[PDB]
Image 1: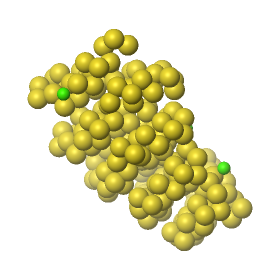
Image 2: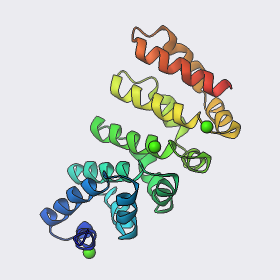
Image 3: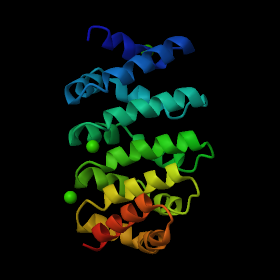
Length: 199
Ligand SMILES: [Ca+2]
Ligand SMILES: [Ca+2]
Ligand SMILES: [Ca+2]
């Protein structure tokens, strides 16, 4: 509580140990439900967190992604605050990262954002995420494939405009190809996503 302003102030500290300590403490608060998430937002954390998505330090990048994922695990208005802070262009670019850990974490944050209402889903679409998400359905990495399926399934839970955008990005044949997957969990998830898109 009382320590939140000092934590936020230190999210751009010139001392890297001080920055990382505040960032680690910040994600813990943002895990305590929507009221705590809102306290983090209202303390001004979002601009500093979005700036950290450009850090060359992959450790800081990962911790910033966790913090944003946790904020985006809240209500639709809390997701919208993440969107309004400009997180989506950086997240979409990180879908092309060669670091599988960073990629998984960027996908996680994007999927949480796409778990909001139709306005939050449409912002993900408008940020250009669909082509990369569809391409990731070809990934040999089970964890990445699982998260790309999750992201697309979340988007396909939106309105007809959102489902049609998923169709136009070529998701259908990629999900049909997964029906022959040896992995039953993936096959069933892909089939459910197909049904959502075609509904
Ligand atoms: Ca500061
Ligand atoms: Ca959610
Ligand atoms: Ca829905």
